[PDB]
Amino acid sequence: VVRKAGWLFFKPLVTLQKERKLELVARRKWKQYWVTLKGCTLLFYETYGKSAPRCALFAEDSIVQSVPEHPKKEHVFCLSNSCGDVYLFQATSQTDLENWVTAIHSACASLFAKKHGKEDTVRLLKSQTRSLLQKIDMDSKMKKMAELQLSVVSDPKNRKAIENQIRQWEQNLEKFHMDLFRMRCYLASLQGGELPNPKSLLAATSRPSKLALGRLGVLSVSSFHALVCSRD
């Protein structure tokens, strides 16, 4: 069944190319489509209806963020999927944007709960946030321990070996923070609350990550999400 439907301007922004590196989509432009949300799939139709979609967007495990700062358009929101892709959408109003964000996050939370074989979605989400928080605490401590051990190592290759480990700990932490943010987005959308502060998530981006996002040309929660996905 359809959870929501309505006109939307669409524009692909980022994609994961071979070698698994992110890149801005070339020749990207705004096109309007009558869009429908069925399950966690966004179907795009070139004409209003109530007849085959021109394309589909499988949004399982996605994150949606409003983009009020967009310089030329209002009511823009951004969807980053679980594959390293980032998309832009323009709703018809602020209310319409909120309805879309709520709809997509609710569908995703639903599928998420379904995959974990649970019917109490809110409880699963809360349980997840607690778990992610403990993992962050645990891995943060492991990372400091590794760094302390590296401090006395002079051996060249032995040095890099521990650094490689430190980087993994660092990447695992970004992923946990990303999952934590995503879980809070789902919870907020299901309970009518304010979505989690994106600035708080960007504070967890490592220097290497920030540089990569900087070379990409887009530094935000959405591109950060795409970066974390590219490592999967």
Image (tube, grey):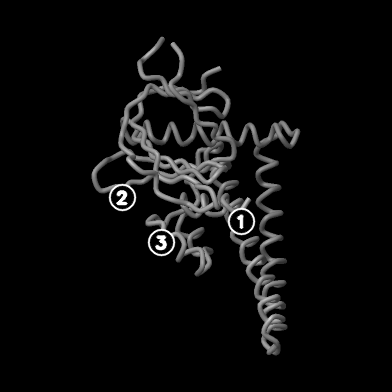
Mark toward the start of the polypeptide (1 vs 2): 2
The amino acid on which the numbered mark 3 sits, given as a three-letter code, is Arg
Mark toward the start of the polypeptide (3 vs 2): 2
Look at the picture and state if 114 lies above or below 46: below
Residue closest to the far front? 18
> Dot 3: within a 10 Å radius of its alpha carbon, few (fewer than 14), some, or many (20 or more) residues?
few
Mark toward the start of the polypeptide (3 vs 1): 1
Q: Which quadrant of the view contains residue 217?
A: bottom left
Q: Secondary structure at mark 3?
A: helix
Please say if the residues under marks 3 and 1 sit with CB atoms less than 8 Å apart.
Answer: no
Task: Indicate the position of residue 144 as horizontal and vertical percent values.
Answer: 67, 77
Task: Indicate the position of residue 73 as horizontal and vertical percent values.
Answer: 26, 41
Q: Which quadrant of the view contains residue 174?
A: bottom right
Q: Which quadrant of the view contains residue 9?
A: top left
Look at the picture and state if 62 lies above or below 156: above
Q: Secondary structure at mark 1?
A: helix
Please give the residue where the numbered disc 3 appears in the rendered image. Answer: 215
Which sits in the foreground, 71 or 99? 71
Give the residue at x 48% y 60%: 202
User: Looking at the image, is mark 3 or mark 1 nearer the viewer?
Assistant: 3
Task: Indicate the position of residue 84 as horizontal and vertical percent values.
Answer: 52, 46
Give the residue at x 36% y 37%: 11
Please give the residue where the numbered disc 2 appears in the rendered image. Answer: 69
Look at the picture and state if 26 lies above or below 200: above
Task: Indicate the position of residue 5 as horizontal and vertical percent values.
Answer: 43, 22
Please give the residue where the numbered disc 1 appears in the rendered image. Answer: 175
Give the residue at x 57% y 54%: 228
> Dot 1: within a 10 Å radius of its alpha carbon, few (fewer than 14), some, or many (20 or more) residues?
many
Q: Quadrant for the N terminus, please.
A: top right
User: Looking at the image, is mark 1 or mark 2 nearer the viewer?
Assistant: 1
The amino acid on which the numbered mark 1 sits, given as a three-letter code, is Lys
